[PDB]
Image 1 (cartoon, rainbow, N blue to C red):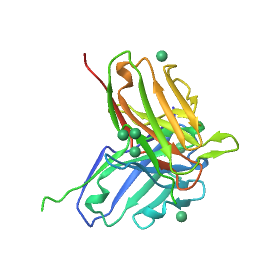
Image 2 (spheres, rainbow, N blue to C red):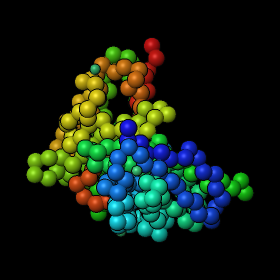
Image 3 (cartoon, rainbow, N blue to C red):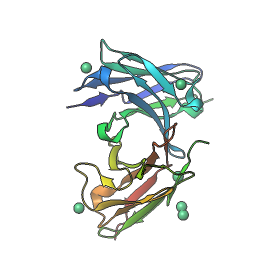
Image 4 (cartoon, rainbow, N blue to C red):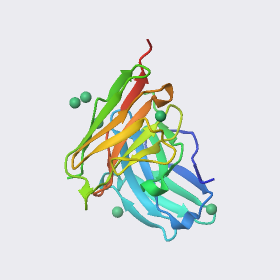
Length: 232
Ligand SMILES: [Cl-]
Ligand SMILES: [Cl-]
Ligand SMILES: [Cl-]
Ligand SMILES: [Cl-]
Ligand code: NA
Ligand code: NA
């Protein structure tokens, strides 16, 4: 099976560098772009950059151009990201992933803990947390600052991250269920306004939900909505 394997944690000092690894297996490493993504509680997910392992070509989010360096080692099928000049602002989980919906695949993420005791499209999710009782409906809005449509298709996806699990694709192009996603999920919307619906909610559905656009570079994500079960 296709896997992207990342170390669990790195505990590091301010001002150091750290090298994160993403060991791939189960597919031809050289032939598919890999992306790196930063997650924090308050900013949700942030696209760092991408590398094509076949030739080593990279693209970076302007905001991470000085912070991140992406490389690839074809001999070990491993991609690497170095974070330089670490500060408290770099404490976060970092994932490697294939982000195009049709190739969706995520690593489990490396927690980097920086420890010293002493015109982009914006996506807004609403609500940012909610508790719903078993059997009831959850409805989550994602609104974009500009249109994410092209040729009648919406370049927006929803991701789910269940507790302790990697993120996964839930719905692609606004309204299509990814393979293996249960029918209780549905997605609607176009243009700037999108909605995820889940009904009837089950215990397995407790997770954080993120929307994402990939109409324009850089790809951007909403800040996340955490859904819990409201215990009766
Ligand atoms: Cl670049
Ligand atoms: Cl809200
Ligand atoms: Cl179902
Ligand atoms: Cl948000
Ligand atoms: Na390989
Ligand atoms: Na609102």
